[PDB]
Image (cartoon, coloured by chain):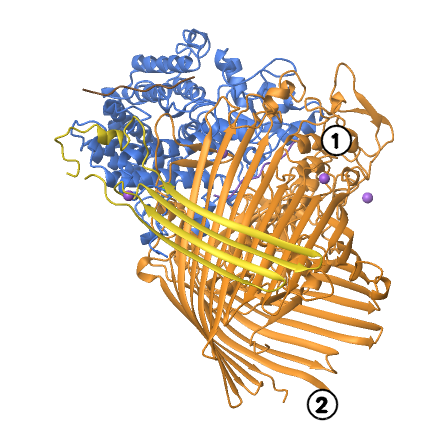
Chain colours: A purple, B brown, C blue, D orange, E yellow
Amino acid sequence: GGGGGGGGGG
Amino acid sequence: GGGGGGGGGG
Amino acid sequence: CDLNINDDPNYPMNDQVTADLIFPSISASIASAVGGEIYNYAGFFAQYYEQKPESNQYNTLCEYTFTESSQQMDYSYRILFAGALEDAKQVLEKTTNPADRFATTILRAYAFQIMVDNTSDSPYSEALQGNANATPKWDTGETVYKGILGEIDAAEAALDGSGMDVPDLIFNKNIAQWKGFANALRLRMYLRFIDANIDAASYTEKVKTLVQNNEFFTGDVKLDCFLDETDKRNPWYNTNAVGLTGNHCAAYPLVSYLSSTGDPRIAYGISKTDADGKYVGQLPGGKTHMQSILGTDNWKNKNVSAIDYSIGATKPVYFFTQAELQFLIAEVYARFHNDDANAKSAYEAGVTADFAVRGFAGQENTILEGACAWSAASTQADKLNLIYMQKWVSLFYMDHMEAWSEIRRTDCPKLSSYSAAQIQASESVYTPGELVAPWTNGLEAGGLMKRMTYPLSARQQNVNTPAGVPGSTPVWWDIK
Amino acid sequence: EKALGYAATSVGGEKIAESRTSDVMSSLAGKIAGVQISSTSSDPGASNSVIIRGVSSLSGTNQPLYVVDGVPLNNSTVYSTDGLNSGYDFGNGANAINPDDVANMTILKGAAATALYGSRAANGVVMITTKSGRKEKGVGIEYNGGVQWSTVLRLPEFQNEFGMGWNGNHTELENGSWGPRFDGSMQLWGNVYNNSQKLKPYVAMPDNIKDFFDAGFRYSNSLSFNGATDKSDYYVSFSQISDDGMIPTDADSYDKYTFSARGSHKAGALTFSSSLNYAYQKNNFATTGQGLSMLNSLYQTPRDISIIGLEDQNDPFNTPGYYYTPYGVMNPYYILNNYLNEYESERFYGKFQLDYEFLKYFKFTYRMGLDTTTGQSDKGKPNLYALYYEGTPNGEGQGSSSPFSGETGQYSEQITRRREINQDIMVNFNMPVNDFNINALVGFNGNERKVSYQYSEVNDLTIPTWFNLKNSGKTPIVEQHMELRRLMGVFGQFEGSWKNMLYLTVTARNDWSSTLPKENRSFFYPGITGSFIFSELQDVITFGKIRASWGKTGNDADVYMVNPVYAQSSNRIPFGSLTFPLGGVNAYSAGNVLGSNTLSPEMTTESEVGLNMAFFKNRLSFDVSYYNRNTDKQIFSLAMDPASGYTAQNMNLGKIRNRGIELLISGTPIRTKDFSWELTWNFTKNWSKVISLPEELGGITTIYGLNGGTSMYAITGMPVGVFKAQVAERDPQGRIVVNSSTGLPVEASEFGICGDMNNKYQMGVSTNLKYKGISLGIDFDIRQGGVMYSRTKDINYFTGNAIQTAYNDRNPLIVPNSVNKIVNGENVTYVENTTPITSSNIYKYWGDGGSDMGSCFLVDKSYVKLRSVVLGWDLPKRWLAKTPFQAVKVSAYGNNLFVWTPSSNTFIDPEMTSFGNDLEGNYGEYTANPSSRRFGFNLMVKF
Amino acid sequence: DFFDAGFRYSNSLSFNGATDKSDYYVSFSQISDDGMIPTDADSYDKYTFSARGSHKAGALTFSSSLNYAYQKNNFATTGQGLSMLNSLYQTPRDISIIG
Ligand SMILES: [Mg+2]
Ligand code: NA
Ligand code: NA
Ligand code: NA
Ligand code: NA
């Protein structure tokens, strides 16, 4: 498809 | 430690 | 140099790929979606869970601030149409077995049914043609529900009593279950026309004569099939407890209602708070607000009950739970047969069935005698509320994509009059069990998410895809 | 031999190797007109990218045909297919050629006369020519032994005003710097171990990341043995390179060994020669990506925390279950010491060639070449879950959100096998008539290329540390693959000549390729080439030549693009898969890339014209070329509506066009017996434009990009590589729209285009000093224009470490033009905005992009760079004599020394990527490791 | 009668020369065998290529041999299972094997 990122932590 | 043969049919 | 060497030797000869080799993919590819990324976003929309304070990912889903470009279902659209439905198209040209064609047409029709509940319109009459029509018109949700319901009827009528030769991971060739799924798919779709007010005379008699025959399915309709090993896990767990870190925590409406009804099912899927050992829920969209009102050290993950994934690994994907089947029967008796005796039957059998799946068998007394007891149901509309709520809980951690469809159709739970911030202020004013408009809300129109966006992959490639509309534009069968 | 009628550039081995690069191409980086050369990163052993006159192959074969002697050389690349989570690059196929064996490079740029080298040449050709025989001095022994260091080049520009926190408040465990301003007071930090906690002054540590890196060290030893006779020659050469780059640990390793024997002999009439070469390499990479990698873990460090103070594993607070931050990130020292990512590669190549002259005016040449490789990848990562999850804060105390779940460990191993056989069978005819000269050439080409691998992976490791396919209680995964294509063509090249003044050339070739549908294998592409040396009193005009050419360069398709396939079922889901078998049932699915047997061959047409002149006995020289390239009917898996059954269909595309200008000017202002000063200026400007992708599939196709995020396309009207990204909503008047309640911008209804990948123009400026035996050469590389994605900016933004995020001294602000959309039923009304981004939500305003939102992280591709510096001392012969030495040249050098970048770019050397040395690499840089400065010494000793 | 006649073709080539200070040998051998068991199941293909050369200037001599060797085999497996021979001997004396 189109590759997914990931948000981090805070 | 060895190895098995089998017989045949008849 | 022999040139005739261009046959891809990493895949079998097409000649050899027969219908029983393809058909098992339909069931799984569907479940890849309906139990995977779709089940996810429906979960937020139906207000079961929420974004953990100490992480970000589903922010734009809980605050409704995603757009058509966020591709929030492009993946599942590819699976549903280029995975399941094509293989379903192949099976139907590769096997003349009416029992196999029948179960393919049901899995075919179940896919379309889900597409339609997501963007109302969906390609249909022109889909699944190759180069011969790369840009297929998006038929309308009413046309699709119609067409596929006709596909099931035509196909049921073709059964000749022969059995299946295809590997069935769902009902293992037990036709009389597949007929059951079919009727249940009809019951669910028929109730939508009615409450959407289209041909509601016929469909009220078609539901009557359906529920009368009780030719439904036993148990749940599912894929029990997964394993706790890479690439073999339940699609929702694999994505969120493996591919990502823990992101979900329990929402204010679900924790309240369970906690006010004394429901012991509050422990199946919801862990107590790692800080004070009670069940705490987070107001929809409120991650960024709650942290602004309390400290920053005072709304961490320890302050809210996290969703438990322990049970996720092997947990099957469900297409039609039993507990929900009953709750649809108990709705039909209740409001179309005037049969308050047989509604109470199905209503309890609903509540009981779900208490079985979660492992609290023999405990329905907890709510079947206190609070959610059918006695205390005063109005014959206080009852539908009782049926409609218990269906909401019946589907938690089971079939979210419906729990968002049944929340849209029967617009129950009620939307709470009070804003998120007001409920945070004086919790007193909150009716337990009522949705809450997300604290942040990208919807220029307010109110709750009524649909998913069109696939970006279809926006860029199909000139005929409908124009983008905001999240508050309802689907063809939600009219309030 | 300047009968050539299209642009081309020659370089001399000495120039190639003087920069002492471990590679042949990265030295000519900014030095030749219309040869775009960029290494993927400063990680040792990585790939280099060489694209000539624009991207033409919309995916993804744009390297030029490297040809050694003159057998095509394998230029295969070995980088990761998942740059977002496991990033690495292990090499370019040509990286294995030993620069000290180069005698003459000649880059043919023209797509018009290519029939000698075939279809691959439409990307340009890099003709290399290896050094050969003597007699000389001297036993025939050269030795260059060098020693260089490497230092970090650009780190992102940090803020030293606020330390560890989130929302603006103080936190003990954060992975970013949204904390209060720097008191100097003493606060806690880090996890709690055995009822104790560390406690440090809250002050900025401005060098804490700069201090993390060491000084990379690399020794290199080369050696050649040479001699010749009146009927033979023989060259033997060896070379060793051993790099340990600037990241701490052996994690960034590159070892290169080569060997080569090249001999000819004449006995006739008949000549026979043979070049044979072996090339080894062992890379280890410090993986990149969004996961638990070393850089993504490094950048997520508050400004007050001491990195180098985390290495000592005997300090419990640095062990994994008590690391100072749990937020999806691990001690960067522990990552480099316990994760594995290896590659090892053995390769054999060479040629046999049998010249045979006969009947006075004819010659016969047969030339076979073989380029076989075997390469073995091995990666594995610990079972952190079993080692550290129970009973630690990071930990059981982090529930699902622990960085350790579910890292249950993984090990995998892949063995790849490649092999190409090329065969040429030619006959050549060279007869003068009166003042004319006729040179003809007729031949046959044969090419066979095959690749295959066997991959096996194993998850959830039983003994948490040991990496081995027998170390796991769960099912293993197994993959297998092989491609084989073959090609035959017949060709012919005619060369005409008139008193060394006119040079006319006509080429014709016809290929049958195995990758095209059976009823349409054959394609035919001719060409024509004119050279006029309108230079036939002065003594002031040394050389004058004018150039033109009109030619075609057919091309086939990738393998196996015709027939439909049924892959084994598997379903791509976000961050996972569901792959058959399940459970005990296997399954096949209909393949998601629709075949097509109506494909027709690709056809590139080019027009070119040029002009070359010199003056004052070659003390002023310039060369200009204008080109117009059209790559038609390219065979591409073009994107398609998933509702159609497939996700893409293979069809011939339209024209991808590159028009441009290439210009070289060079002069010698001073040239006096003992002292010469040289100037060189080269300028390339190119105009990319996709002309028309098939309409029935829509306008556009994706070349690469994230999901619901910044992706890079190829759109009908536009250049090759258009970006889109989320841009904030504007009223019909100005005017950033913001949320009435939080203050943050409101994403517009679509993604806005935000720029292509291309430079607007590229140029470089070079100068050379010679005084007695002293040499001094300086080269500057200037590339301006375009844009690229940078998670390096993104993550430093998200994290509050980039200087940019000290904007309003983090005081609550109202976005300076903001406005609110006021919707009543159906009426749009904009109000001057009154709501402020509160302090607590300043983080979110930046993490998302600020007023640019997502398009914020498209960075200006543009930089000026101090490419190389080469100080060379050639000892005088008079200093030797009493010694075995026949020449000695001590050399001191430095590469990639300094980089100057607009102003919007405080983040990256723009010369980075995480997506490989070709088209898809122009997408961006997903926390590529820092690029690096290089400098060393080198000792040449002839014998 | 079950067996055919195996066939095998061979081709060799060498190139050779020298001077008073150097020598050069370059060679290529090629073999292809299809043994007397029927089918292509008994196959051997061998290819070699070798280049060897020396050179004296000095005092110093330097030489180098480099060789590449290919082979593709197919073996008509033996054993006690469903293999080809053990299946052949276990044939009655009156049964026609070529039928
Ligand atoms: Mg498919
Ligand atoms: Na995998
Ligand atoms: Na290092
Ligand atoms: Na300031
Ligand atoms: Na044989």
Q: Chain of mark 2?
A: D
**For residue D157, above or below residue D571:** below
Residue identifier under label 2? D538
Q: Amino acid at mark 1?
A: Gly
Which of the 4 quarters of the picture holds residue D699? bottom left
* Relative to C44, residue D642 above or below: below
Q: Are marks 1 and 2 on the same chain?
A: yes
Residue D177 location in percent, x, y?
75, 35
Q: CA distance from mark 1 to mark 2?
A: 77 Å
Any part of residue D298 in sight:
yes
- Residue on which disc 1 sits: D165
Q: Nearer the viewer, residue C327 or D13?
A: D13
Residue D559 shows in this picture: no
Q: Amino acid at mark 2?
A: Gln
Pinpoint residue C120: horizontal percent, then vertical percent: 39, 40
Residue at image position (54%, 70%) is D110
Question: Which quadrant of the rendered structure holds the C terminus of chain D?
Answer: bottom right
In this rendering, would D721 be left or right of C322? right
Q: Residue furthest left?
A: E94
